Amino acid sequence: PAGQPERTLESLLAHLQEQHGLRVRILLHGSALLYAAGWSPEKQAQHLPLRVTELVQQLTGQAPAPGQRVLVLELSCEGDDEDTAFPPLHYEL
């Protein structure tokens, strides 16, 4: 297990929006695309009580596997400079 334990999708989106006052970004890589910005209301995206890791795989339709898994996520963010957005997140399962 790498990084802090997965708490909740609603927590992740709500935390960034309130504590940092920054727009939400999409984490996508093979498995699925995480909701952040789109036609759908922003409040709806943060509403999702599903776990951050479970939600991504559930949207994908892939069940969890035993042992350590290596997954990488890409941050899709619209901005003038690439430095504004953080580099891809490395998370193992």
Image (spheres, grey):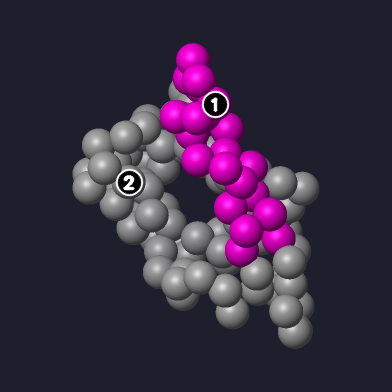
Nearer to us in this view, 81 or 48: 81
* Residue 74 shown in magenta: yes
- Neighbor class of circle 2 (other Cα within 10 Å; few <14, some 14-19, many 20+) is some
Q: Secondary structure at mark 1?
A: loop
Q: Quick check: 23 left or right of 51?
A: left
Q: Quick check: 90 left or right of 78?
A: right
Residue 31 image point, x, y percent: 73, 52
Which residue occupies 77% across, 48% down?
30
Residue 69 image point, x, y percent: 74, 72
Which residue occupies 22% across, 47% down?
19
* Above or below for 77 versus 54: above
Nearer to us in this view, 86 or 52: 86
* Residue 92 shown in magenta: no
Camera-side mark, 1 or 2: 1
Nearer to us in this view, 85 or 44: 85
Q: Amino acid at mark 2?
A: Leu
Mark seen at residue 82: 1
* Above or below for 59 versus 44: below
Q: Quick check: 29 left or right of 40?
A: right
Residue 8 placement: quadrant: bottom left
Q: Which residues are magenta?
A: 71-91
Q: Secondary structure at mark 2?
A: helix
Q: Quick check: 21 left or right of 89?
A: left
Is residue 68 in view from this perspective? yes
Which residue occupies 32% across, 46% down?
16
Residue 21 placement: quadrant: top left
Which residue occupies 38% across, 54% down?
12
Residue 68 image point, x, y percent: 73, 79
- Neighbor class of circle 1 (other Cα within 10 Å; few <14, some 14-19, many 20+) is few
Mark seen at residue 16: 2
Residue 7 placement: quadrant: bottom left
Q: Amino acid at mark 1?
A: Glu
